[PDB]
Length: 406
Image (cartoon, rainbow, N blue to C red; front, side):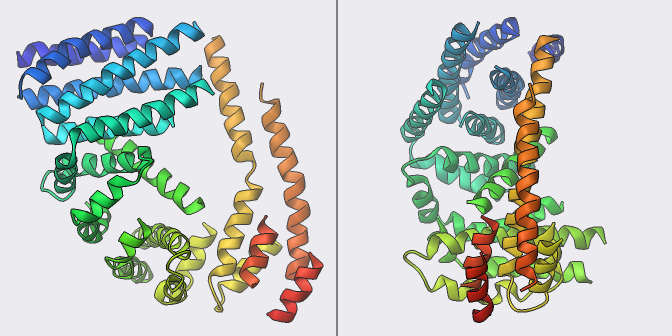
């Protein structure tokens, strides 16, 4: 049997290469039908289940890519029945739980859900509601097990377990999962476990890398945009790690990595500070505190003509406020980000055939406004301060009042 299945896993890869398809999707569905019955029926077997999950990810991912690229009406109703089957696959895998394999496949499913995130939107939202319902059918016991695996001795298991948790919070809309994670003590564990994400980075593989990339993207999104439960276990202590990393960097490539880690920690801290303020305004004492006891290392991370000079002047001493404003201004200028996406879409359309006018029009318009208001911020640099900087990122009257207030 181990030979027959490993033969299917290698035959499967060849089929995928050939596809590189509706027929392939049908084959995947057939595999799921055979696979689903076996998994539900019985608990070697765990390894086979993991292999099946990997195959699904290989095919499911391809299907997702095809959807992104996108018989228009018919293909949508083939995907939705697919997802309906894949949900009842996910449910049997949870009941049957091998655990590491489940975490890997579960993490992949979470990533797929994130990717999915007006009819398509309605369907995605409906799926999210349904996914939550499915999780509820699973119950409280699943979460504790997931939490335990994030801090084990099986290095692939714990990566997949943590990557899965990002997706469970991302698809939630009633916030009961975060309350369950505080109740089990996971956040406290995750103090040392953020230390351990650090040690993870310190110490299948491709899938793990993709999951890490997705987590980084989620962190970036949070920075651009639970805070109580994190702060209540000692966010400052968790931060101490970032300071230590910065110190290590001060003491090459390792130093650069430490700086990057510090930058990652700082964004999270900022996100925590903003959310808490409405009910816990004294967390603005905590932002003012140790947070920016840094030097040079913060200035490099916050930057990684007139606007640059202003950022440099702010990084001199006073406060790290101005820096964040400079980063926001750079992000606003980077309106090619949409232009780059448009160029990628045009390339995808050419590939489908074997239309970037909106993209270049976006980038040029952003360029004109960027240089104009950037020289305006230069004139600002020639002459409540944080709020004024935010407004500038988004004039002489606010400038004279800020220059009388500074």
